[PDB]
Image (cartoon, rainbow, N blue to C red; front, side, top):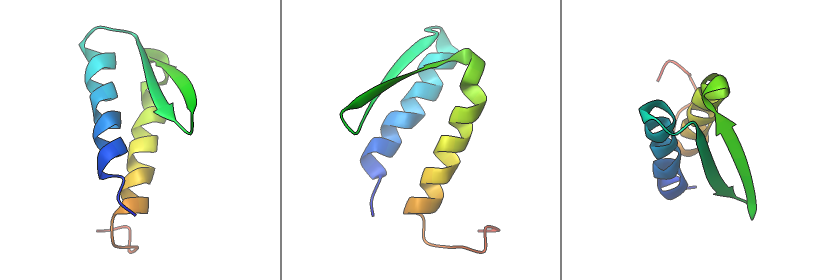
Length: 62
């Protein structure tokens, strides 16, 4: 399990959505999905869930 690549792509979305552009697309499973500054919150979670699926712990306090 190494989302090291797609991971770097998600961080970029945080930079473009809060730098100016309000729209951002992501290539996931041949499926493209849109995100607007209105959901900048549900995206923050998508970034936290991938760190737990690529990290190496479980106590959560890690």
